[PDB]
Length: 294
Ligand SMILES: Nc1nc(Nc2ccc(S(N)(=O)=O)cc2)sc1C(=O)c1ccccc1[N+](=O)[O-]
Image 1 (tube, helix red, strand yellow):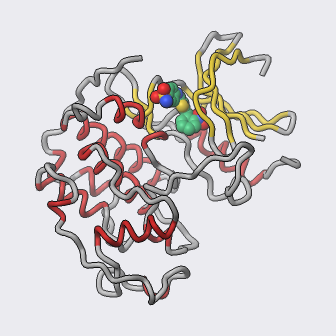
Image 2 (image 1 turned 30 degrees about the horizontal axis):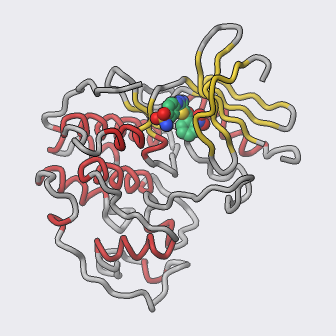
């Protein structure tokens, strides 16, 4: 900590606190995540160093990893705003479609890259997507397969957002696939368009049921194997799928077609990041400059 001047706290998670800080030596401004433990997991710490090699324009750069004094510090390149704040600042007007499209395209490139390197994000949400004045957007705060005991109560405690969680996770799947990130990104795409969260559940069952109420209760026809999943109950209510044109108006058919493919129930039917990049929706993609108030 003596090597870093804390300028201000820029957030807090269940097991980590994030500060904007300055390197007393270099003068470089960074985001510093501080994580508290009785020796700390080497396995979890392992995966970390791995992320250091994942360098891509749409992935926040992990500069350094420091284990010391029973604390783990992650130092990342600093960006000035997250998508959650940007969406809130743009709620009255809405983000222009060309910017929505550019951000979606860039995030898919980022995912295409991590997925081809067998890296999953696992917890995409607007707060973990960072933007800069040049029109770029980047994936931040990648989640580990396991880096700390199943989070359920933080020091001061904070409510975990389930809004972007894929249905297979909610149904108890033990192994996540790259498809979980595509689902989360589709939820974010919908939110940028409508200016309302797609599935705002306040509990795991409410989250699951909100997804079911919109996309219809899944069955073996659309999702083979779903009725044998760990948390599936034959007692789940059976909702009919809602007309998709009601879900994200006034998004055009190209956008709606791509979103429907990102939200397929079956992880194996859900579009890949690579395939999504080739979807007709991106035929006219460009890279606009966002109006950012910092
Ligand atoms: N790199 C980086 N930059 C940031 N700046 C920032 C500046 C302003 C705002 S805001 N609310 O719009 O004013 C938000 C973020 S956060 C961040 C992260 O890498 C990060 C992102 C999410 C969770 C945890 C971490 N983390 O582990 O450091």
